[PDB]
Every structure is written in structure tokens, then in C-alpha cells.
Amino acid sequence: WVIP
Amino acid sequence: WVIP
Amino acid sequence: DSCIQFTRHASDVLLNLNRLRSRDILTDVVIVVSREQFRAHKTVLMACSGLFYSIFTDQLKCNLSVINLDPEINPEGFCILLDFMYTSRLNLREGNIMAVMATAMYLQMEHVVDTCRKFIKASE
Amino acid sequence: DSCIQFTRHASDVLLNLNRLRSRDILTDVVIVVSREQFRAHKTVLMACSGLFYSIFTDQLKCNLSVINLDPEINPEGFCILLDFMYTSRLNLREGNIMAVMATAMYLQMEHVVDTCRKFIKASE
Ligand SMILES: O=C1Cc2cc(Nc3nc(Cl)ncc3Br)ccc2N1
Ligand SMILES: O=C1Cc2cc(Nc3nc(Cl)ncc3Br)ccc2N1
Ligand SMILES: [Cl-]
Ligand SMILES: [Cl-]
């Protein structure tokens, strides 16, 4: 999971 | 396009 | 093999499937969550959820145009997860994390359940 | 927004759609290319090809279970492109590049046409  |  | 690969292809496909969803094109099922209704593509639901995969591979349920979810399921949690299926983006907030995690457990969306468990563990 | 994103989601969705294709699950159209037949999902074809997008948004053709392609289309070129749609991998070879490029132009698959043109320009 990432900060888009 | 890339070499997978 | 000696194939070449287009890096953005999978993302571009999903973006187009979401555009078809937004315009209600070739949607073939209604998911009923209490008083709310959500139109979707059976194939996308199966590709994202272990529960929908099991439902639409059943010889009788594969032909249903309406699927009713368990009454304990929260329509907002379902909406957030349906958006995630079509976009890869999850709108996870303090106010919705419990409903989203409960809905992802029911839908059998393992990666969502995992991030919810981690975000909850960080706040305790 | 304040969304989080699962990097591998789009790739995982496409991998599952390809698994449904391989087991012939919920395929809803046959594409006829001369003597050959190819089963597929209308939504995936629309998401990958400007030609299929135009075909399945037409109020009459959206309901067809069989689509016949132009007789000039090569079944092997179509097969290679159908594989690319479901996998992001393109099996481009000296022996098939002309048929693949002609098929991608007909199907309106701009990124494939672009790499074919570049590979051809390098060999001249
Ligand atoms: O957390 C998750 C997400 C998910 C998706 C599917 N979907 C499919 N799985 C397989 Cl093996 N083939 C085709 C399809 Br469509 C099955 C289980 C799960 N569990
Ligand atoms: O080279 C390409 C690939 C492609 C795909 C689509 N598909 C869609 N386009 C739009 Cl804007 N909305 C929903 C869908 Br499905 C249209 C044109 C093209 N040209
Ligand atoms: Cl997931
Ligand atoms: Cl393309």
C-alpha cells in the first residue's frame, strides 16, 4: 500500500 | 514497454 | 518467453472498466445492501472478492441478476470497497475503518483486511 | 482525496480475468477470425480496443454473442493481441510483426501500433  |  | 510488456496496461484496463461502470455500460448484476443498490460487472467482482468468485462460479447463482448481501453489511463500507475494486484506491478513515474491515472480511478481500488490521493496531 | 492505493491491484485483477478466460468462465462473446473462434469477455475487449469499444456500445451490436472480423485479419495476429489484452505481454517476433501491427491498427490498439512501428523502424 502507498500514498498515491 | 519493458523486458518483463 | 521472449514477450515485451506494457507497464501501464493493467492500470489502463481497470481505468476503462471503471468508466464503463460510471456510465452503467454492460453492468450485469445489482448488489443489494439493505436499502441501497450497486450496479457492477460480475467479472470485476469475481476478480476482487473471494465471496463473489464463489457466488458467480455456482451453476445456479451465476445466472442471478440480483444478489442480496447479509443485512449486517454496511452500504457505505460496501461502496468504499466497490470503489477500491475498480480503482485500486481505498478511502480508509477513522470513522469508516471498522465497517470497511468487516465488509472486506465478509467479501474475502485479503489485502484490504490486512491494511485495516495494521491501521487499527497503530491507533491502539 | 486521502485514499491509500494497493500497487499490485490492477495487475492482480487482470491476472484473475485471464484465469476466468482460460477456464471459459462468464465469457459472453465469440470473435470469429476466418476459420478460428476466440471466446472472451466483452468488457475486457472494450477496455483494450477502440474497435470493440465502438462495437459493444452500439445499441444493436451490444447484444450479439458472435462478432465476425474482416476476412483480411490473421487469426494468429488476433490470438497474440487477445493474449496481450489479458496479460500486458506481447509476443512480438520478426515472423509475426506485420500481422500483429495490421491487426492492432484494425482493433485500434494505439500502444501496440506504436511499439510495432518502432521495432520495424529499427530493422530497416
Ligand atoms: O482476497 C481475495 C481476492 C480474490 C479473488 C478471487 N478471484 C479469482 N481467483 C482465482 Cl484463483 N481465479 C479466478 C478468480 Br476471478 C478469489 C479469491 C480471492 N481472495
Ligand atoms: O488504443 C485504444 C484502447 C482503447 C480503449 C477504449 N475503451 C474505452 N475508452 C473509454 Cl474513453 N471509456 C471506456 C472504454 Br471500455 C477506447 C479507445 C481505445 N483506443
Ligand atoms: Cl484485496
Ligand atoms: Cl494498446
Image (cartoon, coloured by chain):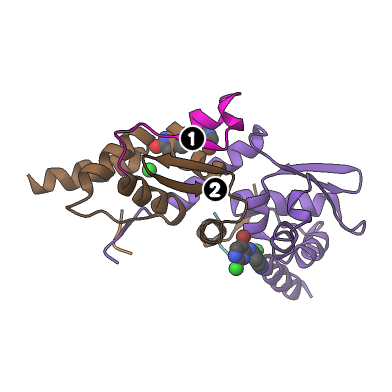
Chain colours: A orange, B cyan, C brown, D purple
User: Which residue is at the front of the view, C70 or D24?
Assistant: C70
Image-quadrant location for residue C29:
top right
Q: Split into 4 quadrants, where in the image is the C terminus of chain D? A: bottom right
Image-quadrant location for residue D4:
bottom left
For this orientation, the residue located farthest to the front is C35
Q: Split into 4 quadrants, where in the image is the N terminus of chain D? A: bottom left
| Residue D13 rendering spot, x and y as whole percentages | 50, 46
Q: Amino acid at mark 2?
A: Leu
Q: Chain of mark 2?
A: D
Taking the image as four quarters, which one is ligand 2 found in?
bottom right
Q: Is residue C69 magenta?
A: yes
Task: Judge from the rendering whether residue C54 lies leftward or rightward of residue C106; answer left or right.
Answer: right
| Residue C51 rendering spot, x and y as whole percentages | 43, 32
- Crowd class of label 2 (few under 14; some 14 to 19; many from 20; radius 10 Å): many
Residue sitting at 55 percent across and 32 percent down?
Answer: C56
Task: Give the total number of marks visible in the rendering.
Answer: 2
Task: Judge from the rendering whether residue D14 lies leftward or rightward of residue D41; answer left or right.
Answer: left
Residue D44 to residue A4: above or below = above
Q: Which residue is mark 1?
A: C67
- Crowd class of label 1 (few under 14; some 14 to 19; many from 20; radius 10 Å): some
Residue range of the region highlighted in magenta in the rendering: C53-74
Q: Chain of mark 1?
A: C
Q: Which residue is mark 2?
A: D14
Q: Amino acid at mark 1?
A: Ile
